[PDB]
Amino acid sequence: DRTPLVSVLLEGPPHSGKTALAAKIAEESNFPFIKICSPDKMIGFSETAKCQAMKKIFDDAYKSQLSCVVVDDIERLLDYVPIGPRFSNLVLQALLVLLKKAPPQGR
Amino acid sequence: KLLIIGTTSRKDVLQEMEMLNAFSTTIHVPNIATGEQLLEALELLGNFKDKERTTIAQQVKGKKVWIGIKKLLMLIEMSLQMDPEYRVRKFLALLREEGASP
Ligand SMILES: [Mg+2]
Image (cartoon, rainbow over all chains, first blue to last red; front, side, top):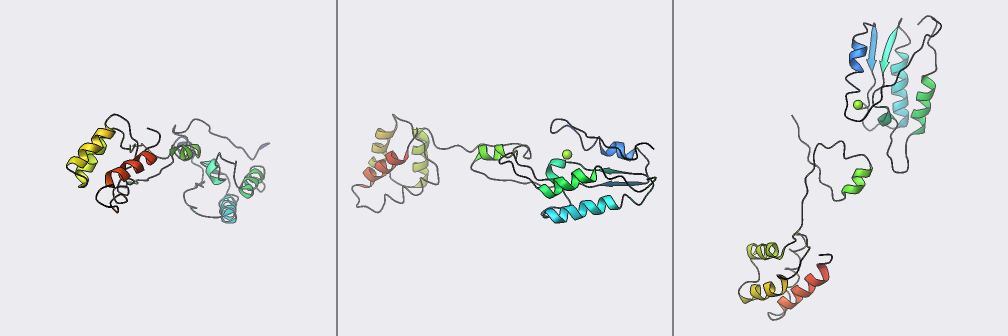
């Protein structure tokens, strides 16, 4: 209870299985509420739509007793392309804020 | 099932955007390099024949050429508008001004 919120990051080379070793951990937890917020269900959205979808998927996780959420392929959520560089700022800010916001008491 | 075939003309730029990991293989489409291949293409396209062919060979066998195949359906059809005496010369001149970087 000193730490209600935790996080972890899976890293490696490309083409190595970092989305089938992150679903098998979530599946074998037997938590009540489990979700997956991937980048293939929001093809073509602008920045604000992505922010709203992320906010909703996180809000629905604040109304249970203990939950797990998977954000796979970060570098595609905030569009990255080595030339430039170029990317979205609003999504990065939303992420950097949402990883430090403790949920209501006892959850 | 599914199958996607994409065609591009600039591989390096695509390689820079990290868009060459998504594709699962790659094929390479070359250009006419050896003179014999150019002669075969002319023979099959149904154009200059008889002694004309011969003279072309005499001037092209001892050298290398570099020309695309959509660009050789225009030179033939751009050197046919002259009188029936200078067609060969105009074709050779156009190829020389085009066949750069052998
Ligand atoms: Mg992945």
